[PDB]
Image (tube, grey):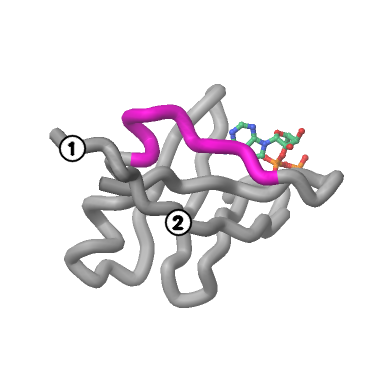
Amino acid sequence: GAIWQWRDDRGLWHPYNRIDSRIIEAAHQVGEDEISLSTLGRVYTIDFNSMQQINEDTGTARAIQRKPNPLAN
Ligand SMILES: Nc1ncnc2c1ncn2[C@@H]1O[C@H](COP(=O)(O)OP(=O)(O)O)[C@@H](O)[C@H]1O
């Protein structure tokens, strides 16, 4: 239903991997405040109240955004 993206240091947007985007979307759809995500051996908090990804070790916050997926399932 959705493709979530995160913003890099050059200001460019990157799609989350497919399963991570599913995890984020499912939490967003039910109104969660936040969901934890692990990728690349890192742990991120996805904070829906601020629409940011937060690295739980470094404190870096990055913007996230949601695009609709047109593709019919
Ligand atoms: N969800 C993500 N998936 C893959 N790479 C990411 C993701 N978020 C950030 N990055 C990249 O990984 C590196 C580390 O980013 P981050 O975890 O935010 O820590 P920091 O910037 O504090 O070192 C950067 O190159 C960044 O662009």
Residue 43, how many percent across, how many down? 51, 40
Q: Nearer the viewer, residue 41 or 71?
A: 71
Residue at point 22% right, 52% down?
A: 26
Ligand number 1: quarter of image: top right
Q: Nearer the viewer, residue 60 or 24?
A: 24
Does mark 1's beta carbon lie closer than 8 Å to ligand 1? no
Q: Amino acid at mark 1?
A: Ala
Q: CA distance from mark 2 to mark 1?
A: 17 Å
Q: Which residues are magenta?
A: 13-21
Residue where numbered disc 2 is placed: 66
Judged left or right of residue 43, residue 60 is right
Q: Nearer the viewer, residue 25 or 35?
A: 25
Residue 72 image label: 1
Residue at point 25% right, 46% down?
A: 1
| Upstream in sequence: badge 2 or badge 1 | 2
Name the image quarter holding residue 49.
bottom left
Label count reads 2
Residue 23, how many percent across, how many down? 29, 43
Residue at point 37% right, 29% down?
A: 18
Q: Amino acid at mark 2?
A: Arg
Name the image quarter holding residue 12.
top right
> In the orientation shown, which residue stands out farthest toward the right?
10
Residue 46, how many percent across, how many down? 46, 56
Q: Nearer the viewer, residue 54 or 13?
A: 13
